[PDB]
Image 1 (cartoon, rainbow over the protein chains, first blue to last red):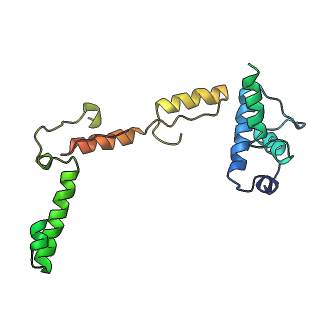
Image 2: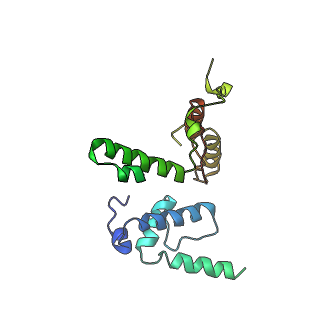
Length: 74
Length: 51
Length: 49
């Protein structure tokens, strides 16, 4: 597994919002309605969300923009 | 409070001023002094004291 | 979860069955119990909003 977490800390900086973003992605994946942007390898949603966030694709603004677009499209 | 200000200092006047300030605050608070002396005594909700 | 929650225990067990992963804070029963203990002794227990 991903033993150490340093890339997510650098990608967030505050180190307290990174876990929040990871958990927000994980809960959304668990409930459904979302697709993993990164190629999954039969693992937990937490690890997949962490990898997607650290890949430079998920942020506190990307998720918010996507949610706003989805809400406005209704 | 005025009398404590009018008092001639020392520990007695200090205690008097403290009591006066405390009274002024408790008056500013909605604290009934009689509330310390209880009137109606609540008994336990029966599920608070197991048999 | 690892505390006295009863109605939260049931909700959490149901969620774990359903894979929801959510806990409901509410208010601890021991809090109301201590409030009563205050009301049990000579002081009213009243909590503002």
